View 1 (cartoon, helix red, strand yellow):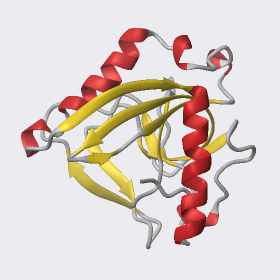
View 2 (cartoon, rainbow, N blue to C red):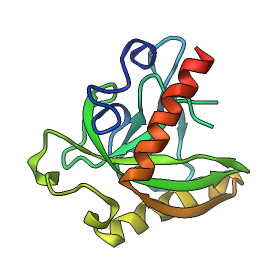
View 3 (cartoon, rainbow, N blue to C red):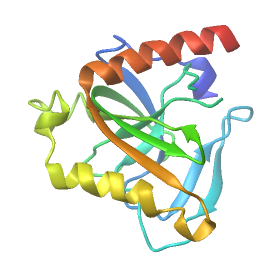
Length: 172
């Protein structure tokens, strides 16, 4: 499994690895299976929405009983199971069915388009809104309730990554 076999990053928490599961623009929700290391179709979203970001996980992280999720803003979406060196710039805070389900927002290190993106204030506000709204509504036809706490900055993101990396060490 890229989850188990890779280190969290080449320079955590400044640069992490993101293992991409879902390319920006997919209505199919793919997940990396931790045991087999293969891509699985978790579900087809019940509504005609698409993932607004390249969506994945950081290797060797464990969060709150799952890998820590990362959203990577890519101009051209990558293929599932691509590794991206990503810079954390933000932290999305939502709770899904009582459980905290925070997500890191990151930019690709090797796309110079995002070179001056270093914190949440560098992101177009309507983009942060479109992400929050996606997670607020995407499971509404499945009867789930997601509460969205909002966003925090890069420093918070990076704390939470270091925290999830040690939680992985405790569990494995």
